[PDB]
Length: 131
Image (cartoon, rainbow, N blue to C red; front, side, top):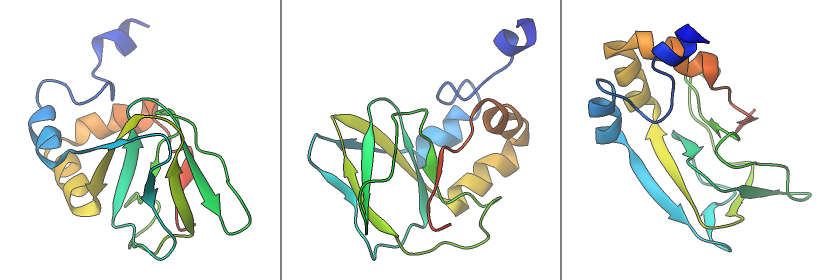
């Protein structure tokens, strides 16, 4: 508890990495009824929700994507290369997702790997796009 509080989690880029993150940070407000992504679109960047909820309508039907805790995207660790979309990403309610390409992600993690340790530790992708 002491180390978790004294450490710098993925609360949203803290003093240090925030400089690089905030730079490559691409905020996106997705209102209730707006489509963030659609089948066929390439996902060369992960999408992290700050607060709210989103629904991805897959060929068959919506899958399951919570709010912020429902982290998802195209992680370099899991996947080596990007890929097309499997379904249609439709926002559920007014939210604010952030898009970040693998390049930017690797950069921030390269300059400040210590953060990733806690970020990937406290944060865990809830949904994996493109398998």
